[PDB]
């Protein structure tokens, strides 16, 4: 009925009523004519529309509470000296128990990202990686939980040297600025500019050098779909703006990345992230190993991202060639680590928000961030 010191009680059994805690509920940002959004807070039409998709919002909440309790636990023990593998496996072991992993009904939405320093995202260790977290490392812990495909994409940055404090704040503030600015009928490009003005209004000093924080321009937030980490709409972070507005009922992952490098990422290091193309249909495979591996992917991950380690834990061996095949066949897409120029530092803060009819909910919000 109460969580245990080292979290072990599933969020499930903590809220027996089946109703999970809501995130930070915000009133939608006004528009031109000071168009207030307090009319939706209790409109009759909207309230019916909201309570209409209540079971969904409730699932996002179960996952969010899982994310909150897991990360609270990670910040209490993540320390330099631990290998990236020890960290990810310890984090993922907790994440599996609190979300009560159940096939594709409940589990980890994507691999535990823990990109270091100049690398901003999509780095998680593969078997054999001997990398050890250092006192001067700036590590982005980015992991996700999901219930019935309702994905909670949320992340924070970890450091131990106070010299990055102002860099993390610059980015944490940039993220909240995009969260506050986001809303139904809000144009993506606008959320982007907002995020940039703030991000760039910060200047930091790290090891004698001064820098004006730069948003990683080729990185960004994005909309979320059931069992689909990236639904289709992207959230800028800079000045351009695709050509779109956020819509009622949508779900977005508002994330920003700040850097001292060139503010641009590129594929680097060995790949560990892979995900089945949400669009590709059923492809008959006769090649044994490739056929088997794909079956494992469909059974265990569906359209959710996974990593080599997760193939390992399932007892799969000698699967790289077969994984390459799936990749060359375009059935699976590789998602290599995205890093900025060597020597640069990058920070990241991310939250999942629900654009509900009556309000904007920052479901993954917590005491920490
Ligand atoms: C590796 C699976 C994956 C695919 C697409 C996106 N979304 S994205 O393409 O908008 C993206 C890519 C890199 C990044 F750093 C942020 C967002 C993400 C993600 O939300 O990070 C993941 C984990
Ligand atoms: Mn993320
Ligand atoms: Mn994301």
Image (cartoon, rainbow, N blue to C red):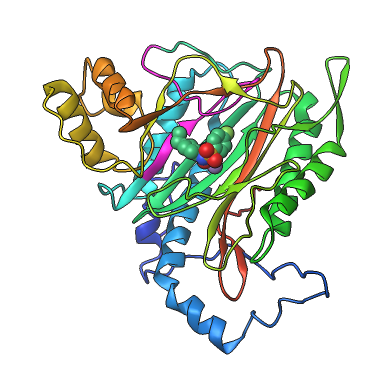
Question: Percent position (x, y) of residue 10?
Answer: 36, 52
Looking at the image, residue 44 sits to the left or right of residue 32; the answer is left
| Residue 35 to residue 147: above or below | below
Closer-to-camera residue (168/278) = 278
On screen, residue 294 above or below 85: below
Queried whether the magenta region covers residue 117, the answer comes back as yes
Along the line of sight, which residue is nearer the eye, 283 or 354?
283
Location of the N terminus (image quadrant)? bottom left
The location of residue 212, given as percent across then percent down, is 85, 29
Q: Tally the marks.
A: 0
Toward the front, the furthest residue is: 243
Q: Nearer the viewer, residue 156 or 302?
A: 302
Does residue 171 appear in this view?
yes
Residue for point 68% across, 16% down = 341
The stretch drawn in magenta includes residue 2: no
Residue 29: x %, y % from top left: 74, 67
User: In the image, what residue occupies the spot 16% across and 28% down?
Assistant: 291
Where 294 sits versus 134, above or below? below
Q: Residue 187, position in %: x, y?
A: 69, 57
Which residue sits at x=26%, y=43%?
281
Q: Residue at x 42, y 38 (%)?
A: 110
Q: In the drawing, does residue 219 fall left or right of residue 295?
A: right
Residue at the farthest bottom position: 44
> Is residue 137 placed above or below 350 in the rendered structure?
above
Residue extent of the magenta highlight: 108-128
Question: Can see residue 76?
Answer: no
> 267 or 342: which is nearer to us?
267
């Amino acid at each position: 009925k109460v969580q245990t010191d080292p979290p072990s009680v599933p969020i499930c059994d903590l809220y027996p009523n089946g109703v999970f805690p809501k995130g930070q509920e915000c009133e939608y940002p006004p528009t031109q004519d000071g168009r207030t959004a307090a009319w939706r807070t209790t409109s009759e039409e909207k309230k019916a529309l909201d309570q209409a998709s209540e079971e969904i919002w409730n699932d996002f909440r179960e996952a969010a509470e899982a994310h909150r309790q897991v990360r609270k636990y990670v910040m209490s023990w993540i320390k330099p000296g631990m290998t990236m593998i020890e960290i990810c496996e310890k984090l993922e072991d907790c994440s599996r128990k609190l979300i009560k992993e159940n096939g594709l009904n409940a589990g980890l939405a994507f691999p535990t990202g823990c990109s270091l320093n100049n690398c901003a995202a999509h780095y998680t260790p593969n078997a054999g990686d001997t990398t050890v977290l250092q006192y001067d490392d700036i590590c982005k812990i980015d992991f996700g939980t999901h219930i019935s495909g309702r994905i909670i994409d949320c992340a924070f940055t970890v450091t131990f040297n106070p010299k990055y404090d102002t860099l993390l704040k610059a980015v944490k503030d940039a993220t909240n600025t995009g969260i506050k600015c986001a809303g139904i009928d809000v144009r993506l490009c606008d959320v982007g500019e907002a995020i940039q003005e703030v991000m760039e209004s910060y200047e930091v000093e790290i090891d004698g050098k001064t820098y004006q924080v730069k948003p990683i321009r080729n990185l960004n937030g994005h909309s979320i779909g059931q069992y689909r980490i990236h639904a289709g709409k992207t959230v800028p972070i800079i000045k351009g703006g695709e050509a779109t507005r956020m819509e009622e009922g949508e779900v977005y992952a508002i994330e920003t990345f700040g850097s001292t490098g060139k503010g641009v990422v590129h594929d680097d290091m060995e790949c560990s992230h892979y995900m089945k193309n949400f669009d590709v249909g059923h492809v008959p495979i006769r090649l044994p190993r490739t056929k088997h591996l794909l079956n494992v992917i469909n059974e265990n991950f569906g359209t959710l991202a996974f990593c080599r380690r997760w193939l390992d834990r399932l007892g799969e061996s000698k699967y790289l060639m077969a994984l390459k095949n799936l990749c060359d066949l375009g059935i699976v897409d590789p998602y290599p680590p995205l890093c900025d120029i060597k020597g640069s530092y990058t920070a990241q803060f991310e939250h999942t928000i629900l654009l509900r009819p009556t309000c904007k909910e920052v479901v993954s919000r917590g005491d920490d961030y």
